[PDB]
Image (tube, rainbow over all chains, first blue to last red; front, top):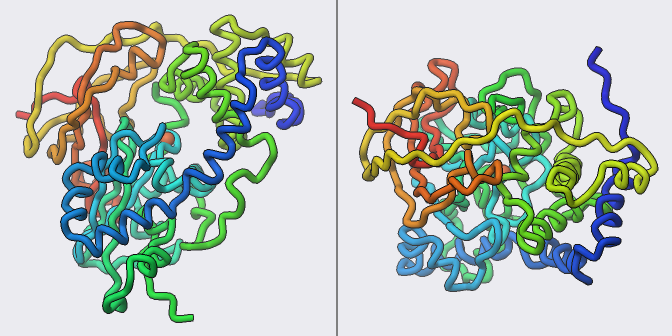
Length: 198
Length: 212
Ligand SMILES: [Fe+3]
């Protein structure tokens, strides 16, 4: 009945696609290797942390992110393929924002980075829209009852980024320091920035 | 297309395999993983054979069971290959002989497409709007949980993009439309069966209609 279709080893099939196109000279020399480096080294959440840290320290920039995110990001030259129209959503003491792409895995590559396996998993895609609080708690983030949870589903071309709340423990920390607190998960809206007392 | 890809809302899944700030490991857990993305841009940008919208649709066009059993990156290897074959760039025979084995692609579309609408109703921020209650067999960018639901607009996009119902098929009727950020109250979408406050969906102008 529901038998899985016969297929060759996945690697064999991945390289067969490559070898086919390459044999016809449809793929530029160094093209594939070039992109790999971009994905691994260039697209990094560190760029997102940078924007957040600055937004905490400089109120003028904060307003730029919240009003014209694309401009603010362009100002750093952190624009890219899956991140041409950026909108930053901020977390107030009574609001928590989370991002999802139920239909696929659309994320702001240049600022957050390539989507992690769990972000593109059937369970996250299906559950977070209906039961955010349950999903977050299981992940390790407990959101109080008086805090409204807003889930943004990346359907069109808009790519989101979350502007977390500034942890009270940082009395006059430097931008450099604040940068280490803002982790990838904070940018996706799944985690809350905490002061590493280790 | 009301296919398995439209997971939002589906009940039965276990828990998300992740603890906040846990180590996700390398960006690519396998050597072949960077290929699907790269070869996609090679077709979109370099060759100009298809659009990103067409890549999404080919994955959606996967046989349901095939979709569920296949991992993320492998879904795109199969998709890009299917497009390559449908555009006439490659031949399934080559793929198979080069792979050394079977290479099942996605199923052929059963919908020509949907041109962009000519009824240009421009909405403003703060307006209540209802999502058109319509069923499109082909590509579309509206999650099933929106049909007939009413929400409020919180942002209209300054830029315009091509209608995905058309361009996702390779039609020229694409046009250009701005997208809106329609905020829906959780209660409106899932009734009492909701653990949250509100969901914000980014919908194309052609999907909405004034609520009155
Ligand atoms: Fe996606």
